[PDB]
Length: 304
Length: 304
Ligand SMILES: *CC(=O)N1CCC(C(=O)Nc2ccccc2O)CC1
Ligand SMILES: *CC(=O)N1CCC(C(=O)Nc2ccccc2O)CC1
Image 1 (cartoon, rainbow over the protein chains, first blue to last red):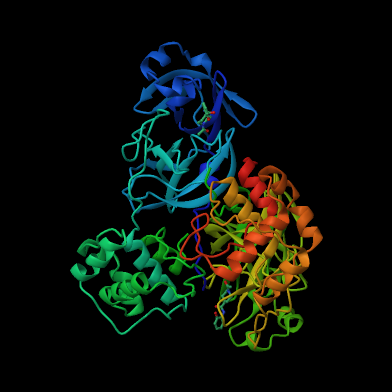
Image 2: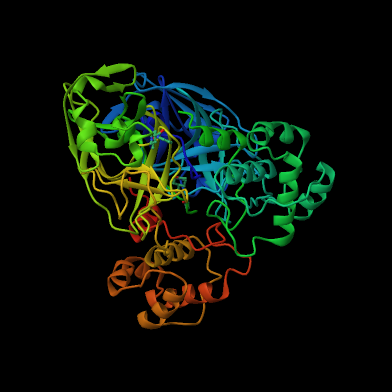
């Protein structure tokens, strides 16, 4: 029993982190096979970041300007290319610790682990969600760029995020491993404001299921609702609209607990309207929305 | 910027987890050098756990009854001994992945990472604190016993916890790696109730400092207090008494933010008396007490 915000074990990703230096900028790279992936802004001076022309900046860079270090050992760069907002540094050595891996572009509401790194060295691991506004709420200081987000399916690491940017509001923006930003964000030091950080309704419901499974049941009530009625209340509280697809996804947790999805919607409606009244659910005083249905089933069944 | 509940990277500990089977019980063991550490209750049947005599139960067990498997490969057990509530299984092979390590007994209020495992296989990593009542609030299903808690100091893993027990209230009890339970708990299926789960005041203050560092400042006020005045309020709210030792420990965060510890005590006093009024601090609606001062400095400075 018990229910924790739980990251994937980071060992397989730790084996992939290197240091990338270009001129005076040091950040992190991901070494898979004979390719090191890193943010293209590694080539920018402070001054460049106001209005960088990356193709023009890159012309001034040769292979030997990209210093790649795995631990204490230097890697030889034998090629470099820009794909969208990432650089792919070809090295002469395949990472011997390369796990089975995929590059995947996640949807808003999907969760992943981040291995925060500095100078190619892991500092910590935490669980994130791709927010509906395509930011993530991370922990990233200077030197943390190139840190990646991932899921593990048994032995296959699905890499979904590389860290690039902090917005003035202290939230985070980055790319998939093809170098495409999540959302409308750019690798430019410019006016970029995040949109409405809406709550991921299906994740809140999943987490209410996890609560019931783990003995926290005080918020169950005598009510039901409909998708349309619930969604009127979701709208008012900046919650994502709940779809039949979300209802279908919650089916296994419904079946396990014997609580109809719409009855749990009715619980959530009352929590939104009435607040927590100073009570907690799984040790939280707000409605947690960074557990997916799959996360709840995973943690509640003990998948490895 | 940003501040997350962050576990240590788990790679070094992943390399140490094995499966231990005795009769029909499967749980986890920690393989360091040529010793596998596991909970002695691996030898109990369900029936035994009501009033086990471990010395007597152990007489019926030989080396060949302890099945130890690292991945797909079996380890040969060449000796076994009971130390307090752990078994030490001597194996004929030193774990080649043994990191630098220490066994340390932590104090209440100290934090650590847990690598939740099932059948010797890592499922996830999360951050815990040794509660003032010597429980931890974990996530542990059947098969998770022998999962360990640890801190990392650069390259040296300090192992502080092995998981043994869930109390009827869904909280967790375990041992250090010398097999001594934290608190008054025993490896018996009996009436064991946790005492008052008091809030770790020095950790709350550390986390308020982390909030200010990261831009969350709405709770700073015009007030100060004294240790004695603050402690009257702490008593009423089941907070640990704040000592001059706690004040001294918070000195670096005081210096960095320019906020006197006692002024931050005054902030915390108002939060305790007035509540959050529906506001959040670092995305929480309650006062977080599972970040130590050292954790805040670590995360806010980017140590690896
Ligand atoms: C995220 C990361 O690790 N980065 C991106 C920022 C640079 C950096 O120092 N850039 C910078 C330029 C001009 C003003 C401020 C500022 O942080 C380091 C690597
Ligand atoms: C923590 C862990 O992984 N354990 C401890 C419990 C046993 C187990 O199955 N014991 C048990 C006996 C009788 C009734 C219930 C119950 O869980 C598995 C390993």
